[PDB]
Length: 440
Ligand SMILES: *[C@@H]1[C@H](O)[C@@H](O)[C@H](OCCNC(=O)C(F)(F)F)[C@@H](C(=O)O)[C@H]1O
Image (tube, rainbow, N blue to C red):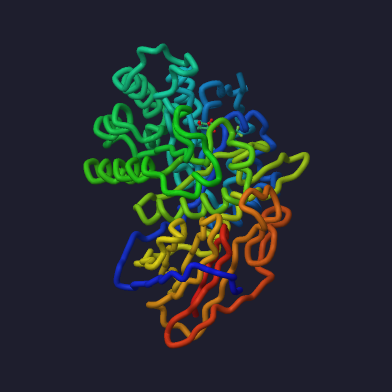
């Protein structure tokens, strides 16, 4: 490609500037526990949904919990989870190769019912595929729903958590746990890590780009800019890790609250946001991510049902770019001369296969860019482009010149070499686009 009047920026790759190593199970999705009320959703029979997950990664994590986990009640025979639903989830995990984070009902359920449900999950799914149980979702927001009274605080929650933990461990001596399954904060997450650091495997935190309802309204323009609250919360998590030894995973995230915002969450801009977010958190030392979704929600990566079929929504294509990059070690990638295109981001990666890759997100809505790439020595680079004709498009999204098809079927159909002369490369990118470069 060539662009009309592009902003000419410099990208310098430094193979000696070592960052974090991306784990092979970094990618992931978060779903409502209420989906378990239908044993045909997370099922070996659901070959469509299993195909979408395999395309997002050979390894990844399925997280089940969410606000419906305070209303879902296990029974060995308001939503009900049966042995049959847990048996079918086991077969779904076998078909996808993914590992499981499983919510237990601390909001409305009993310690003894949680221990009974955990025992059946451990009996059926087993220790290798079960990563963690979580004891409630967003306990700091229990009062907003009246699930607890306004007086409920960290002290109260810690009492609940200990009662559930003790009851579960009696039934399941090897039960693994994560928490506290909420947004970063000083009154809940920091004291949780201090008190329970010997009882959990990792810290589970949540992130939504939209702020409180009294923040300025979320637009595509705002979604593309840096989020200083995200940088702060991520620093907070790094310090918990230094203090307690506990790594962190982002177990529930998406663009906007309450199932997302029409004209923002369901748009190609969400592919750029989600792809960029995956790399920003991996570079910060996060162990992984779980994009919330289900049904036909505005922000869901995968939409549909077993009866009607499943489709890749725009956000899925951001996650697909990450999937095709693969795992490896992050490297130095500094941008210069980039003040008139400030929302361009770039991430360089030494792939586990030994090839250098670069993931670029041109999140500038009104500036095409020309990137002069130094610090890569290769006889040939290829580009796969992440594209839609407008940032607010709800469809027309392609990666490598192709849409995702049925059951997550994808492969690239457009081959493009990156122009190379004097040990350097020059890549044009349209406004609001992304690219994955791979060097021989
Ligand atoms: C985290 C919370 O745990 C989620 O339950 C909540 O999702 C509510 C909307 N649900 C959906 O879109 C569904 F059902 F999955 F399709 C999200 C959120 O507010 O979006 C968050 O609070």
